[PDB]
Length: 50
Length: 148
Length: 50
Image (cartoon, rainbow over all chains, first blue to last red):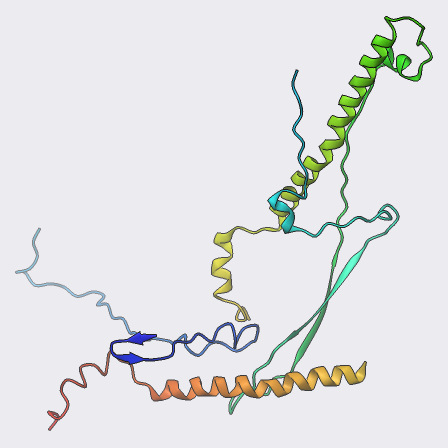
């Protein structure tokens, strides 16, 4: 294929290799995030309002 | 007077689903089986992972058993005329023997054709049994070799 | 039969070393590759990091 101004390969190695074998594919990565949530804070008198 | 349109199982598009073959000894055979032998490939490993081995497996599926049938009753009032026993010599009796023969031929023409339609239906009946729903199959392939 | 089995076994084990390198290449390139999202802004501020 061509992208931008370059000519480059474009491959999938699921069917030729790794198919019907017990090794996971090393392209399925693993992102990691960390969530926070304050539990029992109390807002001051100014910003309590309907 | 109406006619009858015939169908043949080989000229349908469905035939390409299954392999048909005659077997004039099927009535005696006990449970018939088939055997499978497949070999799974293997890729080497490095460092931490342990050294894998090649794997073989043998498996056998079993036969089913079904049938097909029809019914072909014929009346006595004409059966007498068929064999020729009650067949008296007139011009009013042969005219009825012709009618009985034509009736029997029409009936047999109808029943014999019924097995082609029967097979075309049996194929759908059996195929509609092993097929799991697609919705339950697409999310299956994305997770293969990993439900350990 | 035993010879046939040994042959069919070694022909599999030998074939393993091709998928081996094809897997090793991915496994080693993955570690060397930073994510693009964390690189595109890094390349617009080059030479300013003094």
